[PDB]
Length: 397
Ligand SMILES: OC[C@H]1O[C@@H](O)[C@H](O)[C@@H](O)[C@H]1O
Image 1 (cartoon, rainbow, N blue to C red):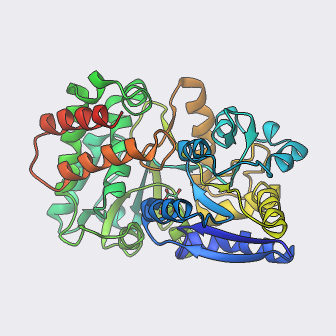
Image 2: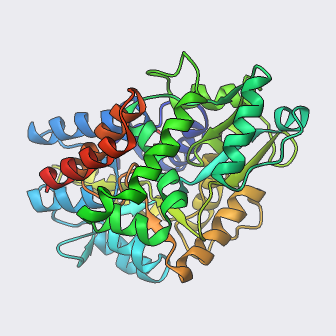
Image 3: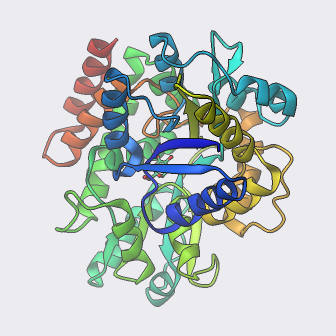
């Protein structure tokens, strides 16, 4: 009987509802799922539990993982042999995924698939409670200046403008979206892809921290330590106007029967045809036993299934990684995501989220998040923040 231990951080809400599609498909194929959930938004907690399980030679069969962390484990030598690469080849994953997604999924210097992608999340979203914006005569903002004007108006009317939880990854999520709009595509690429010292520490970055300082004043006293899905719930219930968060938030809206255009408004954060992508993927470790290897090969195949990725993503709030899945049954926000992905692609605006593990190894992600969260939760000047950011990145290299 095919078996797999699966380590992930999808422990409630729209996340669990989407995961259930995969768990149900696996059991239907007589697969035995050993659940290994590790609660913690953005997966930093999962990454700590995973790391300790590997260093202890107790690798799970499959683990939720992002981008360069895949290759980091590969370089450890804990992944090969690449038993799922045979699945990938037979099914022609190379013609079903974008060059960029495909490259993320490979081990052995780009030669063998060792992880399966299920989706593409987008980071650069604003979610708004529609009755709140209508009640206050506010149009969904398209610029930070429109957002700040709207936030002042809502605050003066006694409404929390921005529902947010201040945890390091969650502060970084807002930050990266802000950076893309305040600085632009090349700036974002230079800072978080190239790690250009001048760009990190310079005047455009200062302006990013200026906008972070504004956003802090729009949050509420319960923010520190708050989980992201609590913040989404605040918008859902009209206890706050806005949330700036990836489209896993749309998993919550959908799971509570709210619809874009009727109960809430989804609009990208300001950018110049930018798109910040995030691919949930599962790596398959070197594991002992033929039943576990059959588990891995079965999971890989299911995760890349055509119908699966349609259904999973409708619930999850993301769009399919698979290039040939019909977007037709998806909502307005997912279609905007798909469209903007194609549009950003051609303009050089399609960029990896760093806060969600696609741009950078965890060491570089950690270094940045820690400075961002320190600025956000203190009275640090924007200049000082940018100087500290550049230095922490530099020291992390
Ligand atoms: O925890 C909130 C989100 O964290 C992301 O990094 C992950 O890719 C999403 O699937 C969702 O789980």
